[PDB]
Image 1 (cartoon, each protein chain N blue to C red):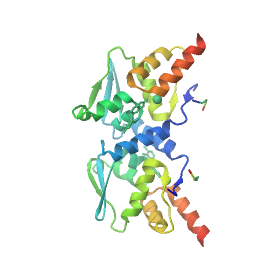
Image 2 (image 1 turned 90 degrees about the vertical axis):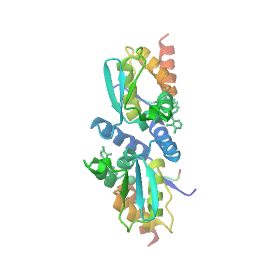
Image 3 (image 1 turned 180 degrees about the vertical axis):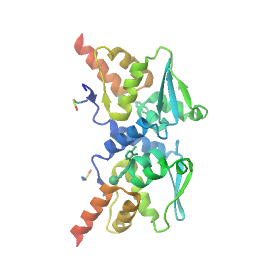
Image 4 (image 1 turned 120 degrees about the vertical axis):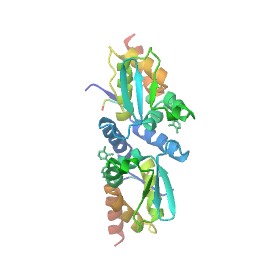
Length: 124
Length: 124
Length: 4
Length: 4
Ligand SMILES: O=C1Cc2cc(Nc3ncnc(Cl)c3Cl)ccc2N1
Ligand SMILES: O=C1Cc2cc(Nc3ncnc(Cl)c3Cl)ccc2N1
Ligand SMILES: [Cl-]
Ligand SMILES: [Cl-]
């Protein structure tokens, strides 16, 4: 086509989606990670995670308002990944990298799994 | 913070949101523009438009499944702007620029209004 | 705005 | 990935 493109559009959309999440606006699901609960938008979770994409395209699970993750999932690792979904920024630290990588593998977030593998390899 | 950032994350999210729109997955509103109907995600519309942001934060309108736009709104201009919301690409042509600018002013999409004003000024 |  |  002969379209023009606004460079900052995708980033501006994601920024506003994070503002709606922070104010709990039109969030339609709560993700339960052991004792912790995280409110989010199903569409953003599906857009970021192969696991959520599979869950919310399922004809019965698409209608659930609560999703319980596997008890081995670390709430902090999930929190870091949810923040990444809504911002493009990943808070990867020596103290959380193992939990972040395991959570990213479970959530099927291949680019996160890749940078965790590389950061771990450099420390070996 | 000491976060790392994935450059293509926002663009990848928007691409997946457009894929969900194309397959009519988790769309929660229909925008009526005279004889034409457009299915979308309320969160994406709010993230792109000052008008939709105001509509869907309203305590009664947030729950509506159908929104009727002003009868002066051109369906093609709306279609072009909805495509822009979900892709960052604007199909701006001599034959549609007036309708696109008027629709962008109504929808409160200031960056689109700006490029339309500039493209019109160059042709004068 | 750019030519993509 | 970059340092933002
Ligand atoms: O590493 C990742 C990130 C990811 C996201 C999704 N999401 C979607 N993919 C294709 N079409 C659609 Cl419609 C969506 Cl929402 C699926 C798999 C994966 N894997
Ligand atoms: O030209 C534009 C594009 C636009 C989007 C929105 N959206 C939001 N703004 C602030 N916080 C939130 Cl939560 C959202 Cl969703 C509001 C005004 C405008 N004007
Ligand atoms: Cl990822
Ligand atoms: Cl805009």
